[PDB]
Image: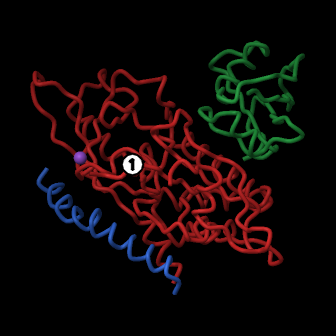
Amino acid sequence: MPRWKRHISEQLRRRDRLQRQAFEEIILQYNKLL
Amino acid sequence: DDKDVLRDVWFGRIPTCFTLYQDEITEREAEPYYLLLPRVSYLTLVTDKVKKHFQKVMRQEDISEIWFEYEGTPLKWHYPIGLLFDLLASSSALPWNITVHFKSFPEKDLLHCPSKDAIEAHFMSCMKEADALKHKSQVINEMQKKDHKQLWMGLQNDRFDQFWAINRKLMEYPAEENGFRYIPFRIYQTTTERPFIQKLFRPVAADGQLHTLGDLLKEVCPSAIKNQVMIHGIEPMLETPLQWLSEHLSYPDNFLHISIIPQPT
Amino acid sequence: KKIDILLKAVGDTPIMKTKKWAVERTRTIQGLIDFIKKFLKLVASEQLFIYVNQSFAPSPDQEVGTLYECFGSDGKLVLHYCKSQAWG
Ligand code: NA
């Protein structure tokens, strides 16, 4: 796999971990007690 | 392989805090609504639950066409959610703080969104404009009306396989060539008076070499090489093949929306 | 600078007498639509679609100078107006 393609894959996964995964559970929890 | 990149881009979410616009005098302060907004979608398409949420604490006479804003900046509903964040709020503390309004619609900054048919129209308009650059609109116009409906339904229902079952045709090119005729891209920049930069650019050089993201910028936006080149929340290497980017890192509207923002702290 | 626009018709719709116009690059499709509705005696409620390359309808907030650089021909941007959806 090319260098640039490996970078993007790692970046997209890093993005999800920092953005989506960080909030997905607590948002789901909060929505229930509303 | 490459399919993994497509899935990550597609299902990309953004933690967003919808706060109703109020003052320190209102009878009751409404509860803020948290939601993961799909990057590749639009505000007026995935905000029915937030509309129902706040319409409960308002009169029937006080409700109108809802509209969102960030830091006093009205949010264009025809811009993809991912693009707005990358350009406006990416270097601020999550979740994305969006203020919710109903009165005082800024008609000089926002286009009205009367229906989801209006959205579907704009979306189809972008795709045809994109394929006009890639294949002279020879691919999308030769599709059935059901194929156009499937592309829209796949985006609205968050169905990856359903959407890409048709979109795969809009990402292929004649065998004799090594890419599209022109790349559907739009370069945004808060500092420039222009809405975005969109010019004709061929993905292949004369000798046959593939043009890179650096080559694109060097040609159409050389005044950005200190700043971040952010696409879908990430900062790809400038050596990345532009042709490959258009195939994998494009939005469902087949456009390559690119943000040029200043470096953070 | 400025760009030249050629307006073409798709009936049934009133025909522009002056089709060749010199326009700004910063003017948008909407302000162009508003200009056309006046000559065609069309009101605000009446819808009016504009097309490029006889295929798609660009957004109302989209500039013409940009569309010219992308889809222009022979130094001018050909546009098509109609009172109904011509091409999907
Ligand atoms: Na915030």
Chain A tint in image: blue
Type of amino acid under label 1: Pro
* For residue C67, above or below residue B63: below
In the image, B255 versus C3, the foreground residue is: C3
Q: Residues within 10 Å of mark 1 (few under 14, many from 20)?
A: some
Image position, residue B243 (x, y; %): 65, 68
Chain C tint in image: green
- Residue B73 in which image quadrant: top left
Identity of the residue drawn at 80% across and 68% down: B206
Q: In the rendered image, which residue does mark 1 sit on? A: B262
- Residue B117 in which image quadrant: top right
* For residue B249, above or below residue B41: below
In the image, C69 versus C12, the foreground residue is: C69
In the image, A6 versus B70, the foreground residue is: A6
Query: What colouring method underlies this structural image?
Result: by chain
Name the subunit of mark 1: B
